[PDB]
Image (cartoon, rainbow, N blue to C red; front, side, top):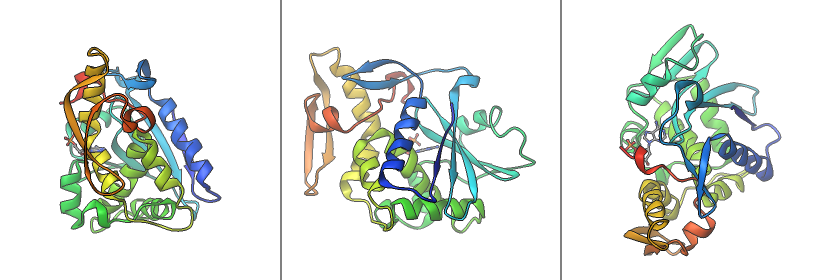
Length: 248
Ligand SMILES: Nc1ncnc2c1ncn2[C@H]1C[C@H](O)[C@@H](COP(=O)(O)O)O1
């Protein structure tokens, strides 16, 4: 199931509609604490969703996402496809963007450590917000090795991370005509998705208590140790759970 988002005429609410549509497009059979639990394994024909993004200038790219972990596999710009250099993306290439004439394998996987090294910048210093997503679309449509890694981190955060956390969706969407640097709280949520997903599943079989705590960074940049499902991040923020059998 594919979804789209257009930057021209975009508003905070239209970005919210987009991210809600993206979450809905990801298959799920179960929910834990009313949070959809992503599937651990899906056949190729059900494993990918396409996100179609158009910038202010009416240029469009299509983004392939693995619905089991919301990872970006690659994207298409006109007649060229670009895929990350990672096992799951190589597999994705057999199913999506099959008709592109030229196929580029990027020099890195989509892991943040590789992307920040390639971009020569850490996530905290890369602007986010709707105008930043516009620029990332332009940058990737007119692909250049020098600028792609940074744009890909904007893209991943504006799609994958926003879908996983209401907080991230809300902070990016409120920047309609301005941009902002993400706080340590955002970095922490991104870093902690797998561990949180894991502990929330364990909690469902352990009276709501985590087996191991998860350390997050709050609004005051303080380390907070999360131990159960009544914590605010579980009750009102995390929006998708990575399946325990799909963590590595
Ligand atoms: N392809 C793709 N899309 C989106 N986010 C990604 C991707 N590859 C890695 N990552 C991010 C997800 C986690 O913050 C970190 C761990 O990746 P790992 O390398 O799996 O341990 O890297």
